[PDB]
Length: 49
Length: 49
Image (tube, rainbow over all chains, first blue to last red; front, side, top):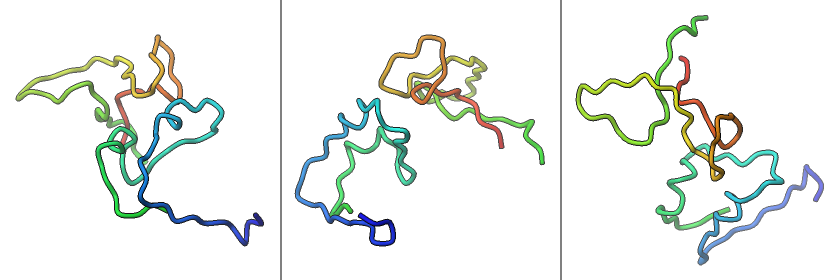
């Protein structure tokens, strides 16, 4: 959508599939700043947006 | 500015006490196997202040 009207989704009750991220060739950037990409799979969270 | 001082940021394992290590091996941070080439998957263990 229009940038001033950017779109949002709440996500919960699901199992993350980071394999697609790690396998992605087409992305220009995949980078996580609050936690390292290897420490993702073993952490659990109460919401994601 | 000063950028002559560097520190080690990646390693395959943690140092034992009073160990010392100066090797500049390319850590296989990314999913693809590094073969003597840098990139978005392979990083240099050292970073400057």
